[PDB]
Length: 87
Length: 45
Image (tube, rainbow over all chains, first blue to last red; front, side):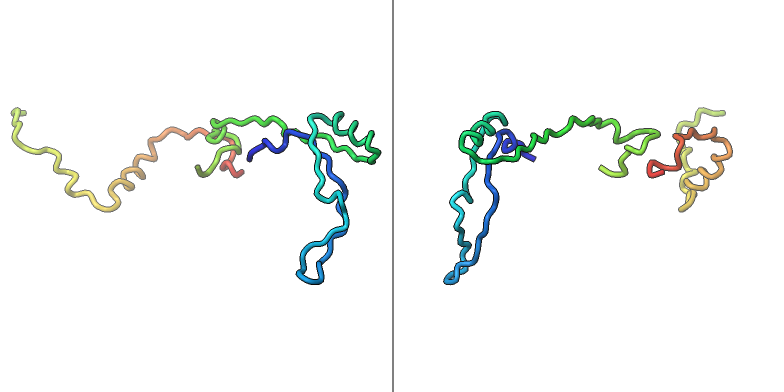
């Protein structure tokens, strides 16, 4: 339930082939950017960095949880379905 | 009528049996007022 890893914008690159090492079976890669992740404060900051470096990018807008209406008294409603059968 | 404060007059309950309480509730039902209704047969309805 912690939300402290959903504060900052990230930039990552498309995933490319990994394969099995013939000797030990480890995951081999030829992608130099496979573990590259960058952190930004705003979307405008992240985009500007990709533009000057010449990378094409697809931005995804932040998903903010909606405010809900929580009522503890609703659990024992008289004529509504929100009454709970157990605590 | 004498104020004979020397006997225990709560001896009736020594004859009650298994269904005494629920038998009294059955007789009492003819007296109760109509119950209120929430509107639905249950919260799951």
